[PDB]
Length: 181
Length: 151
Length: 16
Length: 22
Ligand SMILES: *[C@@](=O)([C]([C][C][C])[N]C(=O)[C]1[C]C2=[C][C]=[C]C(=[C]2)[C][C][C][C][C][C][C]C(=O)[N][C]([C]2[C][C][C][C][C]2)C(=O)[N]1)C(=O)[N][C]C(=O)[N][C](C([O])=O)C1=[C][C]=[C][C]=[C]1
Ligand SMILES: [Zn+2]
Ligand SMILES: [Zn+2]
Image (cartoon, rainbow over all chains, first blue to last red; front, side):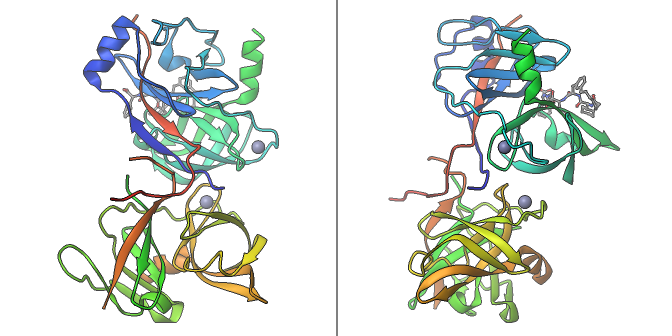
């Protein structure tokens, strides 16, 4: 079927803050991509093969709030710009791509999927250039192949004059090596 | 929750309408030049491209607009009035083959529905089923470019 | 007559 | 620092559905 996505806000500003400090989240989890926040910035996190991966430039070395209190990161790789925690209970995991396709689809924090043409192991180009403002908050989001499998996690926008024309991502391979580290 | 696809009806038949770029498009052979109902009275068609079997009214309430495709994929998906998804391989400008033919009844009442690409973006509007002995094996469709041209 | 809306489909399968 | 908090979700597993009515 075609890739479709929807977004749902499960928590607000004040509840987010209290939860950040407390580190205890009793809310139920659903979905394969979680919208995530710290008191400083908001980004995305993607569950692949049972691990909730996200961008290090967003999560830093922080723990993730869970119903059992904060959870310590399973993987941290400042270089790869990755962090991973055990996937929250209730989440659904994506599976790594096994077809090396060059036609990728980026899911933004607004639940939109945009086509991206793979131009390297970690780069791809937007078929329809969007302003980086639209991409703000999407670091850590998934880059899916036509089969709905994870190819990479969005990391940075390649833009000029404020218009994103390409994107840099973390290919799934970096995940396997980072876990091995 | 807002829908991109509206299930519509006239006294004669029932079909589908698809919201793309703020317009609620459907097939002329279903809507004709009929006006669409709203809580404030009938609203007239913004476009009536009889030649392309295309009509459009301003997007109604409870709907959200679909985005046109830009990946040029040939791997299309047809959404029926029953919410069924059907893989269709694009054969040309406005033709495609069902990866698995179904009785025309399975595609019955879905005209006006959308033809989507691997990213869920609008590729075209389902115009007519191409039958062979009551089995739909291909479909005719109005490319999004035509909708974009009509407006 | 008018074309009336009798139902709606959400492509993402979004609840509520 | 404080913990990273889940403030929302994005679901990819949803398939077309006829929105229920009353
Ligand atoms: C992601 O964290 C963002 C989204 C990109 C638009 N990504 C970044 O901030 C990245 C971080 C980064 C650091 C070092 C190296 C790399 C990425 C990648 C290696 C190759 C880089 C090649 C491009 C050069 C570059 O670094 N580009 C920047 C880009 C430049 C134009 C302006 C925007 C940044 C880049 O992509 N850097 C994310 O989406 N979250 C951050 C965020 O904005 N969060 C929130 C918030 O609360 O601040 C937000 C949410 C909604 C609207 C506004 C703000
Ligand atoms: Zn794949
Ligand atoms: Zn497309």
